[PDB]
Image 1: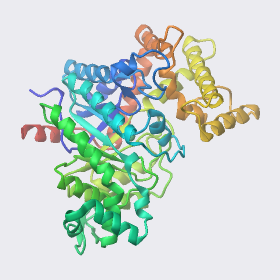
Image 2: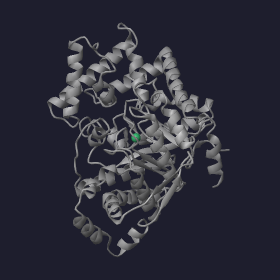
Image 3: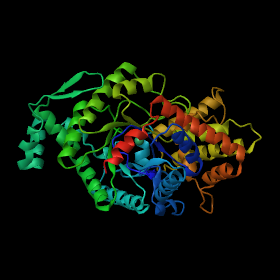
Length: 491
Ligand code: NI
């Protein structure tokens, strides 16, 4: 009998972040149980979660952005595993975005519309890797981790695309040496053909110059991915999978880049189950492009991933509102493009939902008082970050803060609107703000409200379940457990 944490393999499934496992797990597991779903439960190792020793550190040691949910790796993994065992459910415990980066604030800025174009030192690379290993150690120590997403997008060298032909060749020869010819031979003068769900065969060929650029573009990303995957392999006594996070990049993912990246991974002995391309999805927004163009693009990239025994993993899955999915028509275009064989990720949307729910109670109520305190403390914390040029300060944040001010001044927007841009993007800091005794006072209050107020618990659980069911029914994950067991049985 199969239940609790299992590695599900490259099969269609939702994977859902649990920023406050205490309040979110009931509604999610209800929905999973109702639609007979094998789902993932996760948090991002670069931003949302952190090791215990980061979480339990005193105020001020670590940037607000590191483990900003207040939820440790041990905690989310143990709570989710144990909840699932208790509910008789198969789930996958995933470590989302193992992120190479100089800081969590940079990893956050990256997905909040902030132009930083920072460049990492060698010591920084080393420490980021050590941070990741330590995070891994905590995951492994729980006995429950099934799956890791690796994010080395910070290491992608965009200068390789702009090098002079003479500089290019010279660097290529020097780096790759006697392996240069082998590397070119894998690609140049070959017609690659990948067939999508549509039945359209897509043709790709490569010039030497293209291969040389791709190779220089991705060498550091590939090397770090290798180091991370070797460390995971050295520590895991149970089977697991890898996802490549390839989505937090400045432009759309190109077909040839992905062919190359997956193939080079393959050459060094890494076969991801999932790859997450940039397809034009943005955090906190319904899809803002042409649905036909989207389907076309996803059909191609899905076909490519398929030939490497992989599915696409869709990040930035939540949209403009907790109720909007990712826009009308968006799920249908993804399903046609993938025949339903797809992994889809959401996380932050559950806290947006929490906050708007609190905001919807009447002034006079404690629920709404709590909301207003959250909003006020966030606003003031961020003003102070801009004021003191703290770690989250940026021109973009400053503008959003001014936009909110202007709008309330001109009666365009009401005070404490949870839809104000700055709050939508930066409300996450609420869960890591601390009182003078260093407690996460707002996260503690939320959990208290939930644990002690029966009517609040009930309404939130219903909203969480409902949101998870919209995702499940929208992307046809109902009964996906069948393929998960077909994978597991093979072992
Ligand atoms: Ni993501």
